[PDB]
Image 1: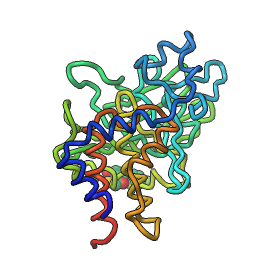
Image 2: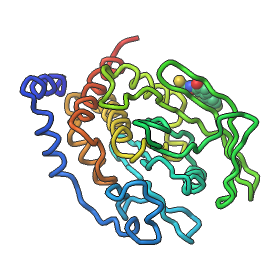
Image 3: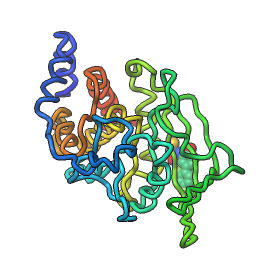
Length: 285
Ligand SMILES: *SCC(=O)Nc1cc(-c2ccc(F)cc2F)ccc1O
């Protein structure tokens, strides 16, 4: 497999930091003017992580339509994702408004609420069936329906109700709970099993809105999730799978949101996940 030996080549030569930096200098730069408006300073978790204006998701409350969220559109793979930051205490209502307005079926969470002794995002869904959440700014109600805790991740069924119309939708929440505080997982196995769980749920499918994917900044682990998903999808779609160049896919995704894949270590891990996930989809059972 092309990338498999390109992987060994990079590894043996300890070249990850050099490839990753070539990616950073090749990466697109587009304006992020809405994100920088003073009125939006507290809608951003990080000052240096902003959605591009061209791809940003707009809340349909036109009032302030801003949310730190980007639409990543992968045209050949026919996949779309919304990558967003972990919601802030003051943007949880916006997050669920986005989920509602974009008709998303799944939310993918790749971080824990607290990591490294700091809060990486707000507790934005209910932890008990009987204790639902009501977001009064956006007129939404969110109920925990069911929770399936597994060794490496948790899947939850949620009910999102639009209070103004009394329509309800079921949202699936896929929470990868075991990414390490430092570095990347030692093996990609649990991450792929997580990815295939999201796929199996139907959440990534074109009949629904884009899956909403987040970590804390919405670029690192979140970038790794989408990048692997799209590369594997392309390797199945193309006549020759070895024509799939992960670096090119990354650069295409970076046209939609800055900074995807934060460290050379995440890049290496992304390669590893795609190579291993290939074995599970280009054959086998
Ligand atoms: S790990 C793959 C997966 O789909 N897991 C999972 C799915 C669901 C669910 C609920 C409702 C529905 F209409 C479809 C569906 F797949 C619930 C829990 C769970 O772990």
